[PDB]
Length: 400
Ligand SMILES: [Mg+2]
Ligand SMILES: [Mg+2]
Image (cartoon, rainbow, N blue to C red; front, side):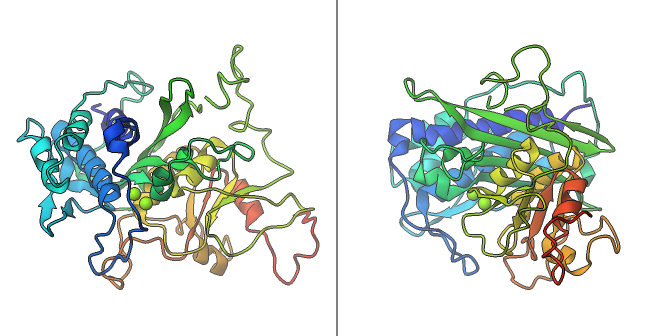
């Protein structure tokens, strides 16, 4: 009925325009940063423009949603706070408004009086984008607003966003780094069961015209509310570009030859645990930056599995992506719990859940995915991968 999802799409686009604008409006390009932000527990307010563009994007989505579905805005949680410390040590509460006491006047206090940088940004946070399909007269679903909580990651991969590389070549379709790794993640889960229901991934930086220098981006979405529904898989990678431009070509990675001979695996820049088994089916493991980008590789079919072994992924990083993945048959299951309860001794209960915190132990790092994750799109592919049998893995040709 009134889709919260079509709105999450216009608004993720409005977040992407801010994310691009800070690189495109010449003046804004200039306020970059210096250090890797997170001495997190004791209030660690470290890198100034990064955190400003972050808080701003979280705020624009919170408020444009407050403004279209009243009541929603208090159920929108995320990684950023909506407060920044400025130069002088003053804590500033970021409210733009709708019809506003100028966002300009608010940004001036964070930007030391910078009337120019203030106005470049307030202009783009208030530009109205119209962005509208594919679930218009099609997936007319109603979900009771009282059961819905939202997890936002405003600009995922801040290192890559800040390093700014526009020129990296992808190994096999997977970008190891670059602006292509940055995503806007907006996940919607069920407050009582914890289960992701709907998701929007927007990559702001997909194609750049090198003559014109402008970037175009792609937006992906899914919904699993007993009906399961998804974005026509499609980024301009495998469509217009040298491929499905004839009639109905749908047999590229997203549809690729069912299953049988090889695992493709993506892992982070810093991943330090293992690898699978070559003469069984492969050892195509790729490094790729972006927690949301690596999930997107699994969604798109470029990778089969995404494994992250440490505790440094959080709910905002996985929720949007886990929901699109559920709408296609996949999910995200906790890593340590699979490594303990060998897979089928109690089945889909180690799917990540997003309503509960972890013991209130770390205080502030209440919302981490503790013993890592494995994101997958086919449970058959997941059941193959986990079969790395210690004490019997030297038969590298596991018939079963
Ligand atoms: Mg971020
Ligand atoms: Mg993040």
